[PDB]
Image (cartoon, helix red, strand yellow):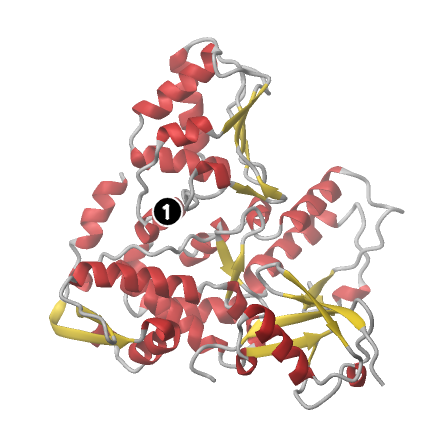
Amino acid sequence: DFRRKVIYFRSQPALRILPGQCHIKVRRKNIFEDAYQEIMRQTPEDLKKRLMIKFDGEEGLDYGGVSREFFFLLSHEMFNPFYCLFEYSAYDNYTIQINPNSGINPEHLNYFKFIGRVVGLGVFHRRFLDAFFVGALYKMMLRKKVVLQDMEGVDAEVYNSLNWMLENSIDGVLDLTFSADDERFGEVVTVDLKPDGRNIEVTDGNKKEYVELYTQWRIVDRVQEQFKAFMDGFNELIPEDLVTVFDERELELLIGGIAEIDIEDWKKHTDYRGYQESDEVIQWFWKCVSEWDNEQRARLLQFTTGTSRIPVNGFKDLQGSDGPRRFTIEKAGEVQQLPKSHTCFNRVDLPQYVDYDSMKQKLTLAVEET
Amino acid sequence: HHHHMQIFVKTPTRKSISLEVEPSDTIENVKAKIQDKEGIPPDQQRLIFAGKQLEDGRTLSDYNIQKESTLHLVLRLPGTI
């Protein structure tokens, strides 16, 4: 369905290249600062014209190549955690989320607007970016609700704590109120989760509510101004009513493209637990993956690891919440159940299905489930 | 009239930088040790200890920074100087 949506999307009036040209000049060594000046001094109408990019002191007749290097270099500066606009996800070091303490730079809201424009510009002009976000951020872009499960990519340790609370008696174990700790550079500041929150004790009786309130605060409330600024920049190029034709997984592929995956690199850097490479089910798994197309494999990757994003040096450098974590397949669960993923460990729990067709279908349902 | 101290400078990329300093070193001195080791120009740097942004002409002991304290390094937005 993604293909049809893309065509439809690209067929809209709002997406037509406007007559004339948009001229952008930057110094390579100053691409962030120069691009910020070049792009913010223009109107959205201006940037919907044909994009023309030149690096100072460098010949630019290869327009496509210059363009591609522009979006590549720029996205690595925008999203460089040093600047605290974005920061790493909780389950790797190459996928990103909004840094809640971005305000340490007083001017951040404008730079979030600028990033939203850069990302909107990439989409508008068919230039993929190295911009891979945590799941919750795509959802917020699409105005969809976020749930506790979305916390895993945002703050995995906090994710585990809330689950432990939901599954275990906390009475007499945890002294807890309807407040949260907002860390900032060594300081701790307290926010109420609900009115008079710090003065309201959390119990086994009301902890579900506490968890849902915490989930909403951490993922959605604490980055609101930043997110609004970002969408403002983004929706100036891509109207919201069009981009919501996509779901959150399609939005990722739309922005960052679809990688051509080296299947052998992948197979070579896979761990097996409870299975061996020679096992029938493992062979069915790779049969299924091989016969799939690039979008279908990217979707398996989103399911297993949180992202379709492949590290520069291949599957050997796959990351998890606690450091390097290889793609891993484990014999676990019963033949009744669907395969189950653990994105903190890049691990798929695959029960030992006894025929190929039920496996392909179990795995397809598991990957497609939102 | 010269005494030493280990401090740590933590980046948002999770990297930790070990610095040997004196309590009476300026914040400016520390940014310039950071430039030595990391090549980052002092004017791009903000240092923060336990929440407060550190001013260039003050000393580590002015902010009660002690042995094995951690400071947080954050870079200014390009174009804001």
Image quarter (top left, top right, bottom left or bottom right) of the N terminus of chain A: top left
Quick check: A283 left or right of B63?
left
Q: Tell me which chain the residue with mark 1 is part of.
A: A
Farthest residue, direction right: A172
Give neighbour class at mark 1: few <14, some 14-19, many 20+ (Cα, 10 Å): some
Q: Which residue is disc 1 drawn over?
A: A247
Res A123 quadrant in image: bottom left
Against A21, residue A366 (above or below) is: above
Q: Position of residue B54 (x, y in %)?
A: 68, 82
User: Splitting the image into 4 quarters, where does residue B25 fall?
Assistant: bottom right
The residue at 37%/47% (across/down) is A247
Measuring 37% from the left and 38% from the top, which residue is drawn there?
Answer: A298
Furthest toward the left, the residue is A19
Badge 1 element = loop
The foreground one among A55 and A79 is: A55
Measured as percent of width and height from the top left, residue A368 is found at 41, 33
Residue at point 62%, 54% (across, down): A215
Which of the two residues, A328 or A252, is positioned nearer the viewer here?
A: A328
A272 above or below A354? below
- Residue ranking furthest to the bottom: B57
Check disc 1 and give the amino acid type: Asp
Residue A86 screen position, x and y as percent? 50, 63
Task: Reply above or below: A246 against A226.
Answer: above
**Closer-to-camera residue (A260/A281):** A260
Q: How many marks?
A: 1
Q: Residue at x 47, y 14 (%)?
A: A281
In front: A114, or B11?
B11
Question: Is residue A21 among what the camera can see?
Answer: yes
